[PDB]
Image (cartoon, helix red, strand yellow):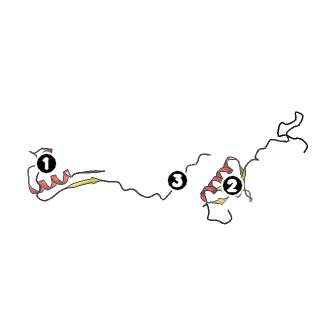
């Protein structure tokens, strides 16, 4: 809370972290039946590209101003 | 699109009237007198409005 990094950062000072997004994860969804998927009696979680596919499908399938919640 | 003289119809009409078609040539078949009757043909293709969308998404 003491340093003034706007002109330059002190040489001893270490940056706390680099800012990155966590691993994208989403509940798995099947497209031919339009349901969430149950695995061993529980919801199955996928990650990264498949989760992005699920999100993209849901985003394309909805209308813009139709729903009050969005 | 195309519009043309109907050759087969003229040939059939001339055959029915009884004219000998073997001796005459194709130009003479096209330009033969038919007696108040005209035969034509045409080709068109009719457009339709868009009502479905098929998206192929890559990754």
Residue A28 — which label? Answer: 2
Q: What distance separates the C-alpha of mark 1 from that of mark 2?
A: 73 Å
Residue B12 — which label? Answer: none
Label 3 in the same subunit as label 2 = no
Of all residues shown, which one is farthest toward the front? A7
Q: What distance separates the C-alpha of mark 1 from that of mark 3?
A: 51 Å
Q: What distance separates the C-alpha of mark 3 from that of mark 2?
A: 23 Å
In the rendered structure, the residue with mark 3 lies on which chain?
B
The picture places residue B29, in percent across and down from the top left corner, at 13, 48
In the displayed structure image, the side of residue A25 where residue A8 appears, left or right = right
For image coordinates 8% across by 52% down, the residue present is B19
In the displayed structure image, the side of residue B1 where residue A60 appears, left or right = right
Question: Which residue is label 3 attached to?
Answer: B54
Of all residues shown, which one is farthest toward the right? A2
Of all residues shown, which one is farthest toward the top? A11
From this view, report whether residue A63 is shown above or below residue A14. below
Residue B29 — which label? Answer: 1
The picture places residue B12, in percent across and down from the top left corner, at 16, 54
Camera-side residue of A19 and A60:
A19
Tag 1: Cα neighbours inside 10 Å, few (<14), some, or many (≥20)? Answer: some
For image coordinates 18% across by 54% down, the residue present is B9
The picture places residue A4, in percent across and down from the top left corner, at 87, 41
Label 1 in the same subunit as label 3 = yes
């Amino acid at each position: 809370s003491t340093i003034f990094p706007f002109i330059g950062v002190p040489e001893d000072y270490i940056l706390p972290k680099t800012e990155e997004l966590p691993i994208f994860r989403e509940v798995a969804w099947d497209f031919e039946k339009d349901e969430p998927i149950l695995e061993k009696g529980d919801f199955k979680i996928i990650e990264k590209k498949e989760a992005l596919k699920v999100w993209i499908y849901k985003c394309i399938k909805t209308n813009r101003y139709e729903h009050e919640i969005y | 699109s195309t519009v043309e003289i109907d050759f087969e119809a003229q040939k059939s009409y001339l055959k029915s009237k009884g004219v000998d078609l073997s001796y005459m040539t194709l130009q003479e078949i096209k330009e033969a007198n038919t007696g108040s009757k005209v035969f034509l043909k045409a080709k068109i293709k009719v457009l339709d409005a868009m009502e479905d969308i098929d998206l192929s998404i890559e990754i």
